[PDB]
Image (tube, coloured by chain):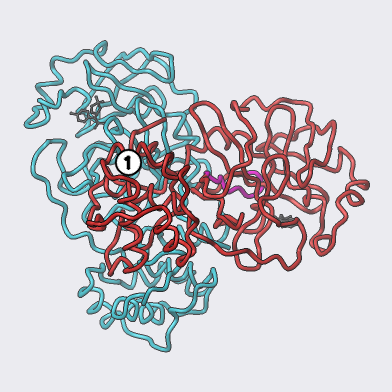
Chain colours: A red, B cyan
Amino acid sequence: SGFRKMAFPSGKVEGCMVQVTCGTTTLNGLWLDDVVYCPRHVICTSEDMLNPNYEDLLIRKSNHNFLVQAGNVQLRVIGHSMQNCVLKLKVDTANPKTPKYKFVRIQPGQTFSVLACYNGSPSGVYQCAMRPNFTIKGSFLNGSCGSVGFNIDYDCVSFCYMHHMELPTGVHAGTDLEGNFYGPFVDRQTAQAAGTDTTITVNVLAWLYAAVINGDRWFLNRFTTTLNDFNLVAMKYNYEPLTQDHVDILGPLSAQTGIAVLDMCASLKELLQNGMNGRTILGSALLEDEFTPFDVVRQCSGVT
Amino acid sequence: SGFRKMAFPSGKVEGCMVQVTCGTTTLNGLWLDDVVYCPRHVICTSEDMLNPNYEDLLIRKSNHNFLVQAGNVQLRVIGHSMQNCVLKLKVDTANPKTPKYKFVRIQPGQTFSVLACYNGSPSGVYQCAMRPNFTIKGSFLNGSCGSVGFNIDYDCVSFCYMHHMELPTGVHAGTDLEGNFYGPFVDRQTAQAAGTDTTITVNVLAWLYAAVINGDRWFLNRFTTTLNDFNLVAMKYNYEPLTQDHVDILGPLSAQTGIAVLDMCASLKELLQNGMNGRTILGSALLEDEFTPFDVVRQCSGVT
Ligand SMILES: *CC(=O)N(c1ccc(C)cc1)[C@@H]1C=CS(=O)(=O)C1
Ligand SMILES: *CC(=O)N(c1ccc(C)cc1)[C@@H]1C=CS(=O)(=O)C1
């Protein structure tokens, strides 16, 4: 019993973190096989960041300008290329700690673990969601760029995020491992406002199921609703609209608890309309939206 | 910017987790040098748990009854001993992944990371505090016993917790790595009620500092108070009394923010007396008490 915001074990990714230095800019890189992945803005001074031409800036760079350090040992760079907003540094040694891994571009609502690093040394791990405005609510200080987000399925690390930018509102923007930004963000020190931070409705319902499963049941009510009725309420409270796909995805938690998804929607509706009246659910005073149905099932059935 | 419930990177501890099987009971063990540490109740059937005599139960056990499996490889047990409520299994091979480590018995209010394991495989990592009633609010399913809690100082893992018991109220009890329980708990399936779950006042103030540092300042007020006055309010709301030691410990956050600890106490007092009036602090609708001053300073200054 008990329900916790839980990150994947970070070992397999700790073994991939290196320091990348170009001139006097230092940040984190990801060493997988004989390639080191890092944000392309490693080649910028903060002067450069107001309006950089990365193609022009890169022309002044050579293999030997990219200093890569795995712990204390220096890696030899035999090639560099720009892919979208990341650099790929070909090194002459395959990382012997390379896990099985994939690159995946996640959708908003999907959750992942972040290994926050400074100078290629891991400082801590925490759980995130890709927000519906394609920001993440991270914890990232100066030098944390190149820190990566990941899921682990048994032996396989799926890398979904590389950290690039803190927006002036202290939320975070970054790329998949192909260097394509999530959302409309650019690696440029400009005006970039986040859109509406909408709540991930399907994740809140998953978390309500997690609560039922763990004893917290006070918010179960006598009522039901329809997808269309629930959605009117969702709109009013800047909740993502709930689809039949969301209902389907919640089926296993439905089945296990014996609460129809549309009954749980009616419970959520009442919570949106009445607030929690000073009570808590799984030790929280608001509605948590960064547990996926998959996260709840995993944590509620002890998957490794 | 941004503030997150952050666990230590779990790699160094992932490398110490093994499966311990005695008869038909399986749980997690900690492999450090040529010793495997596990809960002594590995030798019990759940029948045994109502009123076990561990000394008598152990007499029927031999080195060869303790099956230890590190991933797929079986370790050979050349010795076993009972220390308080843990077993120490002497194996014939030192763990080549042994980090630098200490055993430390933490005090209530202190926070640590838990690597939740099943069958010696890590499932996830999360942050905890030892509560003032010597419980922790974990997330632990059947087979999670022998899971350990830890802090990391640079290269050194300080192990402070081994998971033993879920109490009937779905909170968790366990031992330091010398097998001594935190609080009055016993490895026995009996009536064991938790005491008052009091809030860790010094940790809440630390978290209020973390909030100031990160932009959330709405709860700063015009008022100050005294240790004695604040403490009257603390008593009423089941907050730990605040000592001069707590004030001293908060000095660095005081200095960095320019808010006297007694001014922040007055802010907390108003929050206790008036609630948050539907507002949030660092994305939370209640007062977080499982960040230590040391945790806030660490996360706010990018320590690795
Ligand atoms: C994002 C990041 O961590 N940094 C960074 C580097 C370069 C640019 C253009 C923006 C941001 C850190 C800033 C200075 S550093 O320590 O070299 C890395
Ligand atoms: C605590 C724990 O994880 N288990 C356990 C084992 C033995 C006793 C007496 C209590 C609790 C799990 C229960 C069954 S198991 O899978 O063998 C381990």
Q: Quadrant of ligand 2?
A: top left
* Residue on which the image places disc 1: A254
Q: In this view, does A156 lie above or below B288?
A: above
- SS of the residue at dot 1? helix
Camera-side residue of B236 and A111: A111
Instruction: Assess whether residue B188 is covered by the magenta stretch.
Output: no
Q: Can residue A118 be seen in this view?
A: yes
User: Residue A4, image x and y in percent?
Assistant: 37, 48
Q: In which quarter of the view is residue B240 placed?
A: bottom left
Q: Is residue A177 left or right of residue A287?
A: right
Three-letter residue code for mark 1: Ser
A117 is within the stretch colored magenta: yes
Residue under the image location 58 percent in, 34 percent down? A158
Query: Quick check: B189 above or below B120?
Result: below
The x and y percentages for residue A226 are 37, 53
Quadrant including the N terminus of chain A: top left
Q: Quick check: A123 left or right of B279?
A: right
> What residue is at 20 percent from the left and 34 percent from the top?
B85
Quadrant assignment for the C terminus of chain A? top left
- Position of A76 with respect to A294 (left or right) is right
B281 is higher (above) or lower (below) than B137: below
Q: Which of B237 and A101 is in front in this view?
A: A101
Q: Mark 1 lies on which chain?
A: A
Look at the image and tell me whether residue B162 can be seen.
no
From this viewpoint, which residue is outermost toward the left?
Answer: B51
| Span highlighted in magenta in the image | A112-120
Q: How crowded is mark 1: few (under 14 residues within 10 Å), some or many (20 or more)?
A: some
* Horizontal and vertical percent position of residue B94: 43, 21
Residue B95: give x, y in percent of width and height: 45, 23
